[PDB]
Length: 512
Image (cartoon, rainbow, N blue to C red; front, side):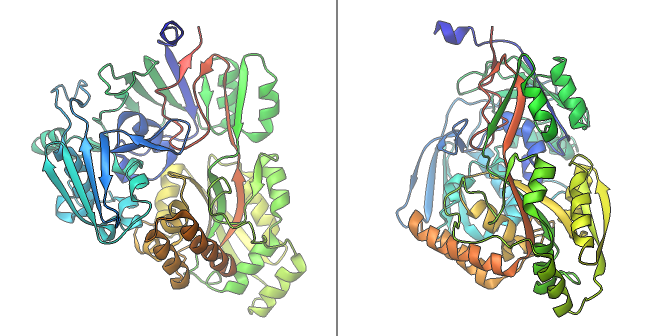
């Protein structure tokens, strides 16, 4: 097409607040890491850009048995892994690559990486080894999963970053050179961009993959920059030095959108932001103390000061853009007198001392707000600040007492918040994504039942009840569902804040 033809060509410079931590997405859990990897690797199925809808990817079609127990995937033929300076052999993707990618996480003998701090965190956290009974390559283009029970989220899970398809040929090559760590540094995938370079804490360069199996990327190159100060990042947009950015200072949004040639995209979001309370530690193991903390923080005021109104008050663990949200639950009321009384009832009439962890990139006013709120009931909060990589590591190991936490949905399903972040299964994995170490049988058992039926209304009933239990238990302080807010130059088209895996750049183009 002629309108289409004009979309091709150019360089996009994207900027964000913290670098990624790996080029193997199975080893990490954070959005910043996935900026790069989500462009490099494909999965068996994928989400249609801008949406939460599943469509084919490295599998062209699939059949699911009507008891939910067997999933047969028919793999795309003629797909080749990237050639780069460090891997110049041209190899066709096949069933053995799916087996490598999954079986390394499933079977500890096939871990591939040396013993050390590397961990398949999502796989462990989710209990994927409990879910899958077997994986078979029936032929070079056919993979069959057999499950130990029905698992409603399973198809959508196969779209998630941790189940990206790595190259078994490349792995084997690195193993024989004793350079296995490079699998996570110098990546090889099938996606619409390939890796060119990664300068830690500075930039990653992606180049168009001319041989991509799907519709070709418009852009020739993407430069993903790390600019940690969000004001500096916005000034870089204002000068044209960068072209699209995440994580704006919300008190600058209004001035940005007034400037010529800047657009600020905004949508409701699939995001939640809260305070973890480590329920296995002193004080935070007492429900009355947690309830006091809940009643002492004015979330309406928090959203005004921290988010400048670009957020909705959080009530349940996941946002109301996802089905199954419990609209009947009332948020805990801000009430200082009640909070004080609760602490007195718990045996702490003069409060106690504790610590909050925060990140160097978050607005510093957040931690200060919590400190101030809790000081009103006699809780003396010390603030400790960490860079992002270190923050993920330390909170992953349960070092915190209180810490800020946040999640962007991977899939539009409550399982991706409730089970992945709040279940006993999740709390059992070390490092953990259940940063409150919340351990409730009654809660977790409802989430297990909800995996085992696929009818959405039936699952909804179980999830509504689960949201009641976690609210009663108050193992955290819910704060906000932030809006997605993304400033960019008006010439940058095709980017979407909606849906999941939003930082894939294959649809983005420069208007000409």
